[PDB]
Amino acid sequence: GEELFTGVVPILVELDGDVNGHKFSVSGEGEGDATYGKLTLKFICTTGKLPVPWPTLVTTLVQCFSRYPDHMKQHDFFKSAMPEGYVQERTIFFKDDGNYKTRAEVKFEGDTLVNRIELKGIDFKEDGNILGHKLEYNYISHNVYITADKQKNGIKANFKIRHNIEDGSVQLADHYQQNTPIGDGPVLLPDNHYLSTQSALSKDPNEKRDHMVLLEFVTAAGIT
Ligand SMILES: [Cl-]
Image (tube, rainbow, N blue to C red; front, side, top):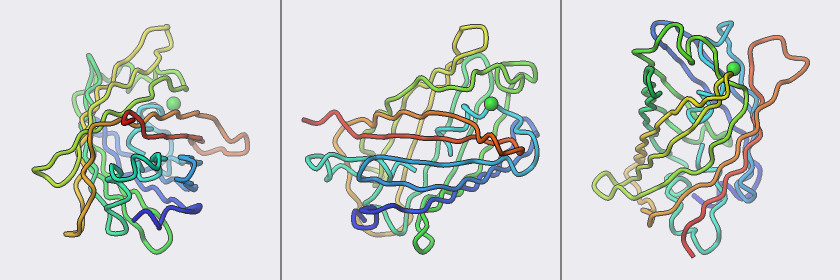
């Protein structure tokens, strides 16, 4: 699996979403360079206006592009599952608001690394921070704490994302994650460690569709 990531890899993302019955679709394209932990992607809402804030979809919208230190390469579950891939499931609990439940398959289709996602959101407040679009277009959170899930031949993670609200407050998004291989092949089950991620959000000044440009750098750490 490692060998599939030594160069620059094209990425395709497809998301189908339904949040309190507000249906939407997102497509994304770009590339990943795992040697540097570097992702460059542009996402488009193909159905018109996105009915939730873009920052709330960042974590849902390819941890196989993380840079694992040489000394930690035996802990890289995500690449080890390739090319057949993995299922990534989350529940994201927005404090004092609704929750997303996501199921994605991350796998190669030829030379392209594909992330295909279904997102279901329920129990949101129609005038809350999410459906009311009260979140700032920025990102402040960084670590994903990974542990092995031996019983499921995979991993789990939990981490908190804080999203800045327009009034200076923060909207917590508590993430619970589980990943399992798609194939029957072997995978690497890691010792406890984390991924340190930074995501920078911007706009394409020539793009009239609702969209998000993302530049991300991700490095594994915590074993030394
Ligand atoms: Cl937004």
